[PDB]
Image (cartoon, rainbow over all chains, first blue to last red; front, side, top):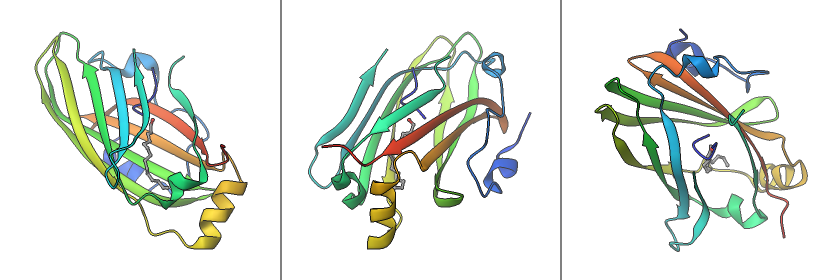
Length: 5
Length: 164
Ligand SMILES: *C(=O)CCCCCCCCCCCCC
């Protein structure tokens, strides 16, 4: 989820 | 607001988001994400810069990994952040492959912060690896972000292991 911008 | 215990009991990826963008009352913004194989040092994915969904396109070799290192950079708005915690639940079809429960720590206001986390892969049978490669996007994750046990963000991902 931390790959979401 | 939802507490960690509520999502820790979920057997399935959610249909929809459990919170709104406006629930991010700390203005936490993810600015860099990098994952690397800790066996080889190979960088597997790096990104730097609504936006609550990411689709990953990996290769079959991804499901032979054991230990992957994640570096996350985020900024924080004008409020202090204590007990920043991410619960990330990876599902295949309608069941949990693995739950990750990471401490992102204390943050001072207007700060830029970096965290390092290690994903140790669940043990996957050959039949489950083949099922995952041949059923792209049946692997899905929920990332639930808590400050002081209150849900402030929910990011979703799905995964293909189908790539050349
Ligand atoms: C949000 O962008 C999620 C980022 C995912 C991190 C990389 C994958 C972590 C590996 C977990 C193994 C799950 C079962 C194969």
